[PDB]
Amino acid sequence: ATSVPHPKIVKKYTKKFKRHHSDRYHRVAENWRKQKGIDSCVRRRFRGTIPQPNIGYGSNKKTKFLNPAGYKVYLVKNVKDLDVLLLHTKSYAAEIASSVSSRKRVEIVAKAKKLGVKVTNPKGK
RNA sequence: UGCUGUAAAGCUGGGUCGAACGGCCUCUAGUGCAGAUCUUGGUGGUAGUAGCAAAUAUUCAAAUGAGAACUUUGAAGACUGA
Image (cartoon, rainbow, N blue to C red; front, side, top):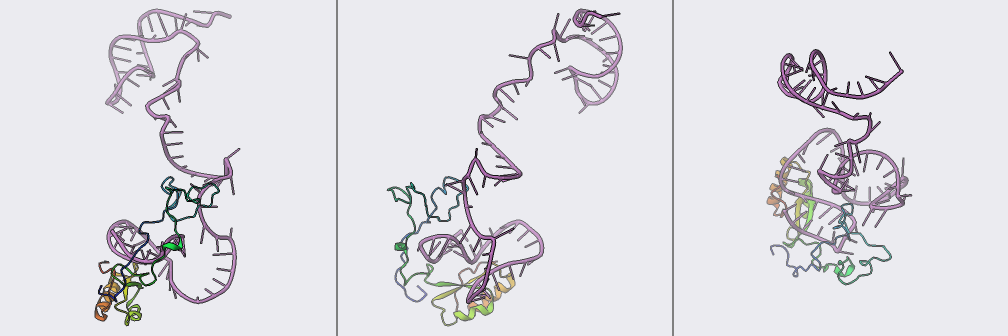
């Protein structure tokens, strides 16, 4: 890791928690919802039903919020926004906002390279 | 196209697009939908399916026309039957 050393990153659940019957009807979005029905086999946790979010799945506090390269990600919208990362260049990477213009985006990439700040999305227009 | 969060969700790459929009500290509410034989609008399967069968009945040729079972003219066969 080019970032500050960290323990090996463990994700307890890497799949997505999909709402029950979001596969069955178009009108049911996958955004997680808790079943509140009296008979619900999912709420009652029958064997064979879907995993549900609970606090036991929480990430280890020492590796939480880290991307695979070992950095926490900070959203940058202009050149000046890079400054708060100046003393945190081995633990915080910059991410350029989607709405920054192509002119200003080139300027942010240049300044980050000047300061030694990692950028997570360099290829943007 | 990926990243973050147990999650509600947040961010990002590519495309489309054309005029406004967001973070943070707070304020406020007509603030979150799968259901209500919910409301309005839109759209399927059914399905090229049911079906288009009462009132005797139509036919040949020419003309017209891009095109004629269905229009017009001629020939005829019929019917209403005062």
